[PDB]
Image (spheres, helix red, strand yellow):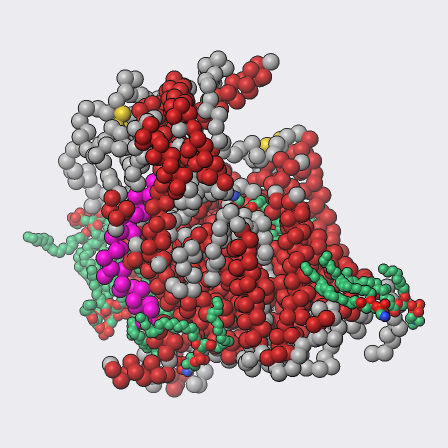
Amino acid sequence: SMMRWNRERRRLQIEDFEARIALMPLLQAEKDRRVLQMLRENLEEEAT
Amino acid sequence: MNPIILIIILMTVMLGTIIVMISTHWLLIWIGFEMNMLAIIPIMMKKHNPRATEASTKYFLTQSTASMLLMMAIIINLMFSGQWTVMKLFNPMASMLMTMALAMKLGMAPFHFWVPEVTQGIPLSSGLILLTWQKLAPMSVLYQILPSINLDLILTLSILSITIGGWGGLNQTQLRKIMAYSSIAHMGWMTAVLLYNPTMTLLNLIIYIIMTSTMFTLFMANSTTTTLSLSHTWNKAPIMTILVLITLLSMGGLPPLSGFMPKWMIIQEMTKNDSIILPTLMAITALLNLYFYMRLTYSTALTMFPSTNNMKMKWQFPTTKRMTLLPTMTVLSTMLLPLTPILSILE
Amino acid sequence: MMTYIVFILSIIFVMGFVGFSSKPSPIYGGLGLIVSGGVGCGIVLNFGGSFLGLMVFLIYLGGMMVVFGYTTAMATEQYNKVVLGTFITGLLMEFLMVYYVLKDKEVEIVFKFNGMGDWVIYDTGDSGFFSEEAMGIAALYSYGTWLVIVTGWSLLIGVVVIMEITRGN
Amino acid sequence: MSLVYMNIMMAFTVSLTGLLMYRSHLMSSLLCLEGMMLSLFILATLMILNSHFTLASMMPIILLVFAACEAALGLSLLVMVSNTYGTDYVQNLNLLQC
Amino acid sequence: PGIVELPSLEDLKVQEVKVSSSVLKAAAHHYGAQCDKPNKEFMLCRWEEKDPRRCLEEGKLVNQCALEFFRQIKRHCAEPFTEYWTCIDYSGLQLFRRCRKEQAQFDKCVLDKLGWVRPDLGELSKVTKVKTDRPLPENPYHSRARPEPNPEVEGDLKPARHGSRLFFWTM
Amino acid sequence: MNLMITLLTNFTLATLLVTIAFWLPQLNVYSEKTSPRLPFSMKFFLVAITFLLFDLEIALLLPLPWASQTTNLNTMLTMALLLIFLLAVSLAYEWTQKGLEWTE
Amino acid sequence: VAAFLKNVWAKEPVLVASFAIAGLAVILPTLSPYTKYSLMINRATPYNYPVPLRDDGNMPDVPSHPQDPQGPSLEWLKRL
Amino acid sequence: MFMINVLTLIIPILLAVAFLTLVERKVLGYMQFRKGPNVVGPYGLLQPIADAIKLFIKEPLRPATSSISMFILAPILALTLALTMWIPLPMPYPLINMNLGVLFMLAMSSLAVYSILWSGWASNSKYALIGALRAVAQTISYEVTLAIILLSVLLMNGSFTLSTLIITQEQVWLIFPAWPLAMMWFISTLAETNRAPFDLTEGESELVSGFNVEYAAGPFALFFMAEYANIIMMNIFTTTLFLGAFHNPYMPELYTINFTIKSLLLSITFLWIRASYPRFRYDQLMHLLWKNFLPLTLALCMWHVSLPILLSSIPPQT
Ligand SMILES: CCCCCCCCCCCCCCCCCC(=O)OC[C@H](COP(=O)([O-])OC[C@H](O)COP(=O)([O-])OC[C@H](COC(=O)CCCCCCCCCCCCCCCCC)OC(=O)CCCCCCCCCCCCCCCCC)OC(=O)CCCCCCCCCCCCCCCCC
Ligand SMILES: CCCCCCCCCCCCCCCCCC(=O)OC[C@H](COP(=O)([O-])OCC[N+](C)(C)C)OC(=O)CCCCCCCCCCCCCCCCC
Ligand SMILES: CCCCCCCCCCCCCCCCCC(=O)OC[C@H](COP(=O)(O)OCCN)OC(=O)CCCCCCCCCCCCCCCCC
Ligand SMILES: CCCCCCCCCCCCCCCCCC(=O)OC[C@H](COP(=O)(O)OCCN)OC(=O)CCCCCCCCCCCCCCCCC
Ligand SMILES: CCCCCCCCCCCCCCCCCC(=O)OC[C@H](COP(=O)(O)OCCN)OC(=O)CCCCCCCCCCCCCCCCC
Ligand SMILES: CCCCCCCCCCCCCCCCCC(=O)OC[C@H](COP(=O)(O)OCCN)OC(=O)CCCCCCCCCCCCCCCCC
């Protein structure tokens, strides 16, 4: 029973990780624009 | 002790030393020192009397403090270098702490205050292991970290070790304390030449281990722990007085013997680097070592002290001790000065 | 105040070390080292070392300091000036260091030290569906093969050594 | 550098100067030795977590295991000293002056 | 040292995908099936340039293709998708395994009205190849010139001239 | 944060219970009552040290449920069985050399 | 060996079950046909990102899309 | 709102500890062919209240203590650890959902021996200290098999997360793949809480529980209610660990009813073990640990390491 169910849990883990992988380009694009937004804000307030 | 357990524990001592000698990671260096101390503690408590428990406790406290200062030096190295390679240290504070930790592990002065107590508290075989084999791993680490060793620190430790190991042995009548203060003076000689030429450091360490192994093996084969018990050796085995004579004359640094080889090569490599005052003061300070060596030769070989009557019974029995490599070590400790350019094999 | 939480726990850590290191008795010294181990565990937990902090509680405080209090109970007897004086000495040295590195945002005892909260030096990214600390500890079995060999050999030898030196013969 | 490293190193030096200045008890000496180990543990852990140096996450565990086995060795030495002299006092360990 | 060069706040303006994480996780398999090419252009540019300032146009193309994806869902299958991400959204771990009938309805309506096929177990973790027009970064670490090495040893090994030359030892 | 709030609440409730249980029975004024080294065992210390060393071996064993996820499974299984075997060998040496005696 | 085994099973059955369970745990994964699949499943679990390749022109085995035929497959894991 | 949740954890813990004394005295009554309390309340329901009010107005006994500070801190630590063992328990949702709840509970239970040790220090009698050291050696002995059985079971779980252990047991109770671990777990948790047949402090085989001995001891109610919080907690932890119930994520009350019924049956099983057997001698439970449980625990630990590898049933990390 634990054999069948842990194999099912591994297949479900792979499905979760593929959802994460399919979302990682969008999250990486948003993260890049996020950090460049915050650095540009810090740069302008450092200039003033 | 079980002989199986004895062999496994000595292999673990040797294993900790080898792990220090081969590993490229600082954690494994620290692991090797931990394994070495953890395995040598039963060798010191082989006979189970309060002097061995006191000696093992003092040895534990000193080597534990040095191991923790070693790990602090390693941690400051991981701060200021982000890595773990056993090479030069990337901070003078880590270099100072590691040089202090290795000075405590070697028992160099002014961290020398455990070596005669611990050497007196333990048997002659465990004292042999402590004064020969336990010098190998910290000198290997000092051999590897020498691009970052502070010169003034290591030479202060060196000359202070030579001077205190000279004056310490002049007051002694116990043989193990004489060998321990001899150890302190010779470790000063080894670390004085380290930043100049560490091949001569390895030469001094090898000649020292040969001569100290010869003296501890003669002291085991005669079962003598004091000066005055060594004085009865002429009436028991007169060849042993000859061998301790030539080995003590060797360890004093007299030519044509091989104990002159290391100090002559050390003076030879320190004058090249424009240091004249320091090898001259080191050479003059080693005359104290020669003085208490000649005291022991006077008490053993050159005169005949009074014996007792019960020695006549011991005339009727041979030595059934395994005097292992004693003729080989006696020949190598005395007649090796014509083979002085053999030192290049340690380059 | 709350951005300085690791710093405040580290001040409690140094105060606990001045507490037990001034050595009132091995019982109260054990208590001070227990409280110090707990707050230093909290310091480790506030960087994301959850497994390593639970290793502090489970192994350090859980086994080793329990064995220290156990052995103290077999070696001390149940029923000063120097302890309290050295306590307030270390406390004043620590608070003068706190006051300098807070009013100046800079100090140099042996190294130069920042005076801001140590939140500043963190990473701004994620680790995905794992802990990096957990995976690095999990690699003791696939990458730390030699490390496991020497650690297990030292522990087996340690069992042998304790049975030798406590035997008395 | 960072502010917490000052306190962890100062904790190491406080437990050092505690360990380097004995009062009476060998147990308090061993407590100072393991406080030195505790400060080393925290300092190594903060470096390794701060650096995201993944493989050295197993380093403080190996430090903890080796030094707690060392502590067990020291407690057994203290136990043999206490069975010899009745107490664990470091002024009873003075036979090796002569 | 030099001044860091940052893009202006006008260059960081894009129409964001202002949905929740359960909305994304519910749509993630069809998003990985359909929005493949700008996403992999962006991740190739992101692992090759090693700089998020050289990847802003590919980030905008990702952020635009994702919006086209959700608009194309919204025109055909808004209600099965809404029921499905609500069921995904209830769970604290956001389990796929608690939501198989709403997934079946969403996949049925998506396959019928849009022709999209959900990826199988193993496909969205494949390593794919990307055809780009941007050049390969020739020095992405901005490394300077390496130091010239020490000379190697060369030649035949002759005996030592007059031996060891240690003070009087003639060999 | 919520963990710290919960720890403070548990510590506060415990200290409140202890303070009540010491000061509430001091309300009733009672009749003031006016009438009127330990032996060492080696086995007690040895069971504690045996605990400490096997607990360090357990500290080595604790990352196993994360260690099974590796791609180097043959090395991982070898070192896992090797640590449990060294724990068993420590137990066997503790057995056969009379270490587990009279606290067996 | 049959007298010793029955004798140790009569006197110390806890140790016999101990050594039997330990010996099965040692020699059994080298004899099991599913020990291959443990390695196969652990190397197929996608923790990191599948960082794509620059299409130079000659990579016939690498797919261009996740749903393409070529590439590594997990049909053995769906079926087993 | 969170403090409401903390209080609705910790106050029903104290009420359940109060009525566990009633359930103990009743169930031990009927097993001993008599009744338990039925006079003080209707069916005995006022017996915990009357007994608590009696214990809180009773005089501090006779003597004084060796150390005031540890005499205060040992019940504080005992009650604090007994209350913090409940916060990661997934029933179906833990109060503090942490990734390492198992290791948290193992560490906080390892910290519980300091209360016994400090109450042995704080007593003036040198014989009560010996009894405390025997109890500390017992508890640290059985913590070894707690740790290794817990590790062997978590090799089928995938993580130290307690909430994942509900997901692990969705197809079968985990007592089916691990019943020898489950029975050695149950007996080792029995020997953890100083519970009969392992209660050597509260019984004989004890150098100090011997009628008209010295030793100022703490207020008995605090250590007693810490001990019963630990008993209910270790039975709930065994229920989560081996007999995990059905969880509908839309109806959490089904899981709460189911784990509550199983935890009550398992605590009554503690009550039914203490009313069925004589006590171990001290070296007999040292024998039971070191020569009986620990070899099987190491063998089954090797088995549960190598078994998901040979069956291709390695659980996921997440
Ligand atoms: C067809 C295939 C076969 C063809 C075969 C052709 C040959 C046929 C003959 C075969 C036998 C050859 C034997 C060796 C050749 C002669 C080597 C020689 O004399 O070198 C002169 C060597 C340098 O003089 P040279 O005029 O420049 O060279 C003449 C040749 O061209 C020397 O030639 P080189 O330039 O090549 O010399 C190389 C170099 C040249 O030397 C140097 O570059 C200068 C450094 C020499 C060492 C300085 C060390 C200073 C500190 C130690 C002081 C030791 C004090 C003396 C001993 C005290 C008691 C042990 O020598 C060394 O590095 C070796 C070190 C010294 C060992 C000499 C050989 C001894 C073998 C027999 C040992 C028996 C025990 C003797 C006493 C032990 C000590 C020698 O002088 C010395 O070393 C002074 C001492 C005398 C050496 C021993 C004489 C050999 C015969 C001894 C028989 C009597 C034994 C009495 C009983 C035992 C003692 C109580
Ligand atoms: C989680 C819910 C509850 C779980 C179940 C627990 C409920 C039942 C509780 C009953 C009351 C117990 C009260 C305390 C009892 C303490 C005493 C006691 O039992 O001591 C244990 C006794 C101790 O032994 P002993 O003292 O009885 O016997 C004498 C021992 N010598 C010889 C050393 C002197 O037995 C054990 O230690 C057994 C532990 C568990 C065994 C697990 C068996 C696994 C079998 C696997 C297969 C084996 C076949 C061979 C290999 C095949 C391979 C394919
Ligand atoms: C860069 C360097 C790298 C490394 C290079 C090599 C370094 C070598 C360092 C050698 C250190 C040797 C330390 C002593 C040996 C260790 C084991 C031991 O203790 O053996 C002695 C043994 C014990 O027997 P036991 O019964 O316990 O003793 C009481 C007496 N009945 O038996 C006895 O007590 C019997 C008495 C005789 C014992 C003689 C042992 C001599 C061993 C050393 C030989 C010389 C060293 C090798 C050659 C030089 C190498 C540089
Ligand atoms: C190969 C796989 C890996 C194996 C290593 C891993 C082992 C895991 C289990 C850990 C066990 C730890 C403790 C081991 C101690 C062994 C020594 C021992 O117990 O000897 C004493 C015992 C007699 O007991 P006694 O001393 O009298 O106890 C007091 C009560 N009478 O003496 C005996 O009872 C005899 C003990 C030896 C014979 C046991 C035979 C068991 C056979 C089972 C089937 C084969 C399994 C494969 C392994 C090979 C076994 C030969
Ligand atoms: C989560 C669930 C937790 C549950 C906890 C409680 C479990 C037990 C529940 C209660 C069971 C019934 C209790 C009945 C107690 C006795 C009541 C009574 O009538 O007592 C008689 C006594 C004297 O009355 P008298 O006026 O003399 O009558 C002579 C008649 N001619 O009259 C008196 O003494 C005065 C009246 C006293 C009434 C006491 C009632 C019980 C109080 C218990 C405290 C907790 C209350 C619940 C809190 C949690 C729920 C909100
Ligand atoms: C005698 C003195 C008085 C005695 C009575 C009172 C003290 C004893 C009882 C209290 C013991 C406290 C133990 C608290 C820490 C336990 C470990 C821990 O934090 O685990 C929970 C969790 C780890 O899980 P994870 O999910 O990985 O992390 C969250 C990230 N998602 O990690 C987290 O959630 C991290 C949360 C932030 C960090 C919390 C730090 C707590 C405060 C510092 C320590 C306080 C205790 C100090 C004293 C200990 C005992 C001497």
In the drawing, does residue C117 fall left or right of residue B299?
A: right
Taking the image in four quarters, ligand 5 sits in the one at: bottom right
| Quadrant hosting residue H175 | bottom left
Q: Is residue G43 magenta?
A: yes
| Quadrant hosting residue H220 | bottom right
Instruction: Specify the segment rendered in magenta.
Output: G19-46
- Say whether residue D39 is visible: no
Picture coordinates of residue D32 (x, y %)? 59, 55
At a point 35% along the width and 32% down the height, the residue shown is: E109
Quadrant containing the C terminus of chain E in the rendered view: top left
In the drawing, does residue H134 fall left or right of residue H40?
A: left
| Quadrant hosting residue H43 | bottom right
From this view, report whether residue B168 is shown above or below residue A21: below
From this view, report whether residue B31 is shown above or below residue B305: above
Quick one: G5 or B185, which is closer to the camera?
G5
Q: Is residue F98 magenta?
A: no
From this view, report whether residue E81 is shown above or below residue G18: above
At a point 40% along the width and 23% down the height, the residue shown is: E75
At a point 38% along the width and 46% down the height, the residue shown is: B25
Quick one: H287 or C127, which is closer to the camera?
C127
- Say whether residue E35 is visible: yes
